[PDB]
Image 1 (cartoon, one colour):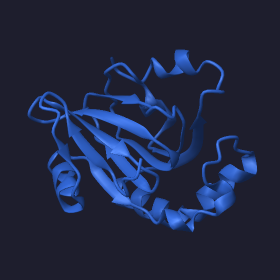
Image 2 (spheres, rainbow, N blue to C red):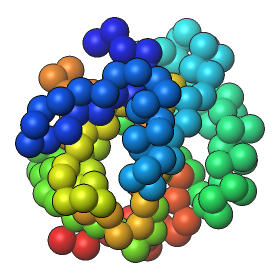
Image 3 (cartoon, rainbow, N blue to C red):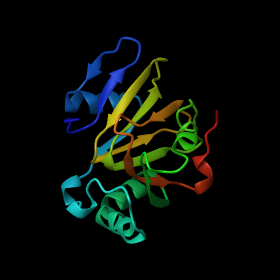
Image 4 (spheres, rainbow, N blue to C red):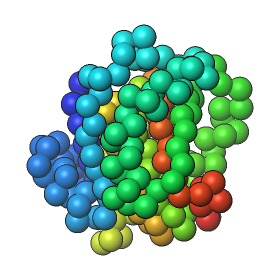
Length: 174
């Protein structure tokens, strides 16, 4: 929907934080890095574009290269790429069930949304799960050892840049 930035839904009580400042203050308290990058830079032929060429991908990484350098140097990341998921993706179901289950990782999990939507569900330090619902222009870093899972929204499609330390730190520890 129409949200500009990320919003939070707390799990048991169902309450919502939507104000910009409170959202980022809240994520700060949970160790979740949040940044808003200037998505208006993205060329329009790359907006809501889900069948991505090798060229389209390289271009996407070219446009946010500065923002990537800054976050990769501030936080110690090394490599990056682009993935897209949609209803048309073969094995969608059999892929998603890997990130729909609660897992953690031994490195941070960093994603920047370019198109579509996602929801990260993160176990807060007080034991309660909260959602971060992401809009394009949203970069989130989910800290090492934090139990979480991932879900698409009802449009079942997302395009993202993944930033990682090593390929080997991507594994779900269930």
